Length: 48
Length: 48
Image (cartoon, rainbow over all chains, first blue to last red):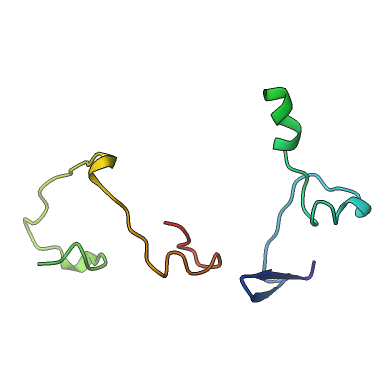
């Protein structure tokens, strides 16, 4: 995503510094909304 | 009369004004929010 929308204010990607965890494949990126795969998702069941 | 109400200014310290340090239990205090605190997440003072 070359642009991020925050409360109606439009920000270009170059200004921002965005960091993410493990990288999903391209087909799965929209499902995760172009973000890293969260660790709670793999740890909550085993913790319980 | 309202020094603590105004924002902190280090230049306003008079000689002999420092007396000590006091600690307050949480149930004796009650925080307050303003418009600026809950304005927009782009603000660095969001929700404090």
